[PDB]
Image (cartoon, coloured by chain):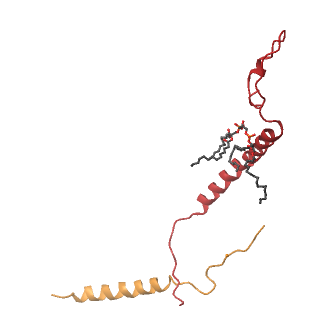
Chain colours: A red, B orange
Amino acid sequence: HGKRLFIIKPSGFYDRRFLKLMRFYILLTGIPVAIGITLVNVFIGEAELADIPEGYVPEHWEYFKHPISR
Amino acid sequence: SGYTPDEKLRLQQLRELRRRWLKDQELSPREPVLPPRRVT
């Protein structure tokens, strides 16, 4: 049936534009951060705890577990 | 009771304008001009 009418609604162009820009920018730095975290976890992730060797005093950053924290 | 003649006339003109305006709200066959572009 050919009875299509005009739906008067406010301009939603600017809302979609802002949402697209914010998503793009968050994603722009966000995706690389996630990929790098995944690669670090898989390949170099988690240093296991061990007793300190006699006569050896460790560095201040060797008392932490996660490589990014170190 | 009933409309005064001026009331009748104003109602007639207003209702004809309103019907014309409402009829102008309909969409032509090409009215939603969509711009195409892509990237069990």
Instruction: Examine the rendered structure and indicate whether residue B1 appears above or below residue A15.
Output: below
Place residue B28 in its image quadrant: bottom right
Q: Position of residue B7 (x, y in %)?
A: 26, 85
Q: Split into 4 quadrants, where in the image is the N terminus of chain B?
A: bottom left
Q: In the image as oriented, which residue stretches furthest toward the left?
A: B1
How far across and how far down the image is residue A25, in percent? 70, 49
Closest to the observer: A69 or A49? A49
Residue at image coords 24%, 89%: B5
Residue B14 against residue A63 in the figure, above or below: below
Query: Which quadrant: the C terminus of chain B?
Result: bottom right
Residue at image x 76%, y 25%? A49
- Residue A34 as seen in the image, left or right of residue B19: right
Decide: is B23 above or below A18.
Answer: below
Count of picture labels: 0
Q: Left of A30 or right of it: where is B27? A: left
Question: How far across and how far down the image is residue B35, in percent?
Answer: 70, 74
A23 or A55, which lies in front? A55
**Residue shown at 78% from the left, 45% from the top:** A35
The quadrant holding residue A15 is: bottom right
Going by the image, does A54 lie left or right of A18?
right
> Which one is in front, A27 or B30?
A27
Q: Nearer the viewer, residue A4 or B13?
A: A4
Give how far across and how far down residue B10 sits, in percent. Answer: 31, 85
Q: Residue at x 84, y 9 (%)?
A: A55
